[PDB]
Length: 203
Length: 203
Length: 79
Length: 74
View (cartoon, rainbow over the protein chains, first blue to last red):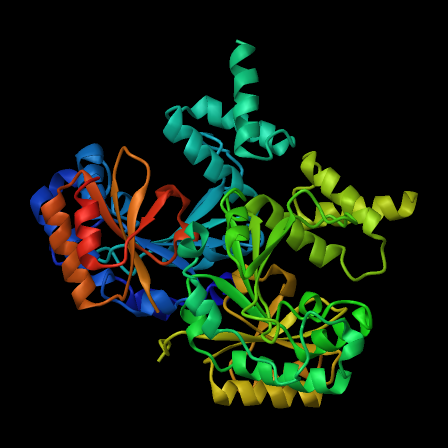
């Protein structure tokens, strides 16, 4: 309720932005039960639909429509044992700054919303902090993602994206950088480089 | 150039959003050269004009129109020796949050843009960090402000408005609050309030 | 009905008190004249401001969202 | 209200960006350009560049033709 009012969304708006699949298949099933060429043809139509909705630019929050290229790579990567609704869950993806994570956790109460809480790094810690929320109308509509981060977590997530492009993805190295950031040791991209040079020297 | 393209602004757009004063007094002058009741009557018209422009909601950046109440307080506070263009420079004020400040200073090269760099603090450190940029068409038009903050500084700026500002404390305490934040000791607005309560008790 | 083109938020707040009354509204003459008149009726202890989105203005937290111009007037007068 | 059509090669930083109006004309332009460029280039729509730091640096273009030529050079 509160977090949705802040970002100008409601269940009716999320329902109207939901794309109904015409594959005749349940999205609870694994990728092996789906035809790659038929899936990619449908993703091309969803991407085309989202590139024509003016309503998206009037909402008081940011969003991105993911490409058919990224969907083709995700199919090849998670085929054949990943669940369809877990793979193609972010074609329409909103991005918001929340005041505190508490207001985002209230979304769990919504029957058609799934919350993936990564605000504490309890599971598979790579330094990134935030909460991802998925609205799904039913088992044959594509899910809609909302990504929430505080300003504090968003800052480190942005520096970590650049360090992971330059140096390559490293789970333990990102986890350790988040400890230095929480300790006041990383206040710029240059400081992260300095801290990294000291971490690499002490090994 | 680059930072303006990123936020969807250009000199032509800023020129069309500039309000021309009918007071017949140069904005390079101090407040003693102006009549309070005439100034406030004009600010009411500028505020009304900005509340009617739909073009503002279509720009790819955030903005706020400041109230006539805030202009009345600013006149009373800075009268009579402050320069008019330094006092009423934020009736239309944009706000853009980012990963760094290296892109922002390049705006100084624009003839009608002034840059106030507070990324290493104000002269009187009150805790606030950011860069403010002012476009002014001529000395007879009201300036337009753009506030730049990294995600890291915007987080503390927010907590400082909520739990610290306008409550009777000295500017000395904000600098201390910013030192605790830079040291990893303040990770929530409630934690800011905790170290403020200890600073005020032990002061 | 929820899609009325680009919208803003009219905010009412008492200067030394935290929190605000917020209303999603369409920018134009009807909103501009409503705000100008309400600012006179409420006095210069209350600030009437227009923002693009509440998630960008953390200094007005917590937001008390209202659903009509009349509801905004009654709630702003209680600040 | 306007959006930004973005073109980016997957393993290479930076993008070609164009301010455009959402609708049939932009949607069909993007669908056709994605086919001509291939699945190594991503054609995405974002609301504002300041919210998408993963596409930095942005190379802003001023026309649909300029966007096509620059996206083919990625």
